[PDB]
Image (tube, rainbow, N blue to C red; front, top):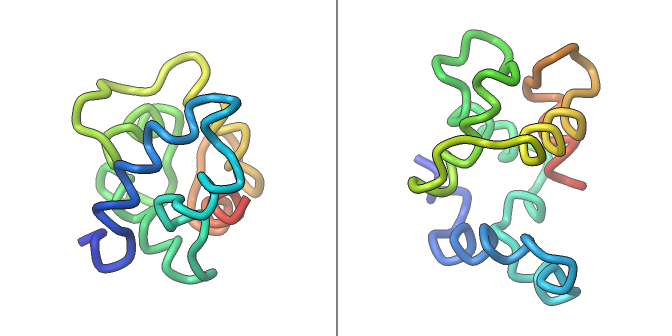
Length: 108
């Protein structure tokens, strides 16, 4: 379950909230989904729900499904979402993201 950590009223309110240059204001950061505003421990628990089968790491292949953990309409990431996420998360890896490299991005 993800509700135990995130909020059903914050997740959907954060999806189409930071998709603009004026949409992500000081207020948008306060009403964020919560992940980016969570403690260094629960975040990793939120990344274990993205992986396909938690084989260890999440390559660009399974990264294109990042829009599946939040929304159920967005097919898969594109030439901007997966890049701005992978190149932003993958820090202690190589062509993929795990846990230590995940929370290091959410907290940002």
